Length: 282
Image (cartoon, rainbow, N blue to C red):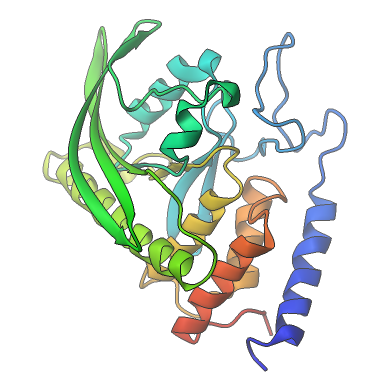
């Protein structure tokens, strides 16, 4: 009953009503708008909340679900790489979680540049990528990890840990287990780099806008929201936080598309069932 079809139906009903309310109007004052015709959104109907946008250059949003603070964004366009790299550096990014598969990134048709697996120069910014470890997430799913070194003249050189899931598991208990393992890997990697900034007295630890893990799949609303929800349940502070809560917070702070597919909500429902966590608010 607490995780049966009736509870699922009421949860879906509330999340659907919220998506309709968050549906972007033409030149919606709630959502970021492109300038001069420059392509801001990788997808037309997947836009960026203006209250929580990290930069006017990017489709990226500050998101805090419960006590978990992250940044959810789309895979940066080619014209956004310099501003994207500037976001990661100014953020002191403790971990960059790339959820696009190696097969999708390599496909030129999708326009997802390979910006974290190779050296390059983008504007006045120079990037160097070095591959570190490989962490198995279970079910044959491997996570390639990289140390991303961002350099800009006059700017502090920033290293950003990267967790890249090369392939995605099939629906079911493989996906919820892999998502559970990925959330632990992203939390651990972030906690190590954040502690490093803390041992050096970095003022970024006192800024709520900085030191936030950055997560993106392709549009930043599917696997990204699935991972962000798995991470707030992994956080000990977020107890009794319902699935209605975290999906509502993810959608009010980015767009009503967060958790786009039933399969992705299904993963959250199953993880919450594993914790005895409520789905609905009383």
